[PDB]
Length: 225
Image (cartoon, rainbow, N blue to C red; front, side):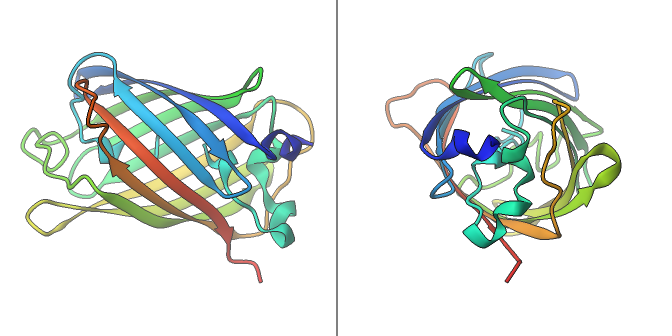
């Protein structure tokens, strides 16, 4: 039933409030998602001025309900099954040899619009590290979100690694641990193990003077034959 809500192009709103080593900030995003093609087009603006962390470190935090699930895998799509009432998405993101983010979001429909409301707290970052030092490249992120059922919370868990390229040529690893739980009390689809293959392309609006990120993203479920 939730899947019916995603057969066409759906407007998306994202709202994030963050605090990283005491640097407070907000981001607003708008765009649209077309789950038929696993396609997301989003533009984010830092509404508080300069973003105190690198945009690439926020991509994963800033709507996996827009994944393209192959027809033969549609029984494994937790995210859509939770809609319209939605789900809580929680993560801990451990930046190797640096701080961590803890995030909590509610993802649900408000009318025809899919809304992602997030709070992010980051702690234990190094002032001259790759995050607070803004040493990460701004280009592309691509990896696999490994999903497994969480029957006790009627939800899912996921784990994955993001290998952020550093401007000197190195890598800043960000190990993600994720849990999603439905907001409503109705049945949800609890999946067999699988993954989401996700590719995120980051760019700039040449006419935009505020601190911002343009995102073109594709998300495809895979791993079941």
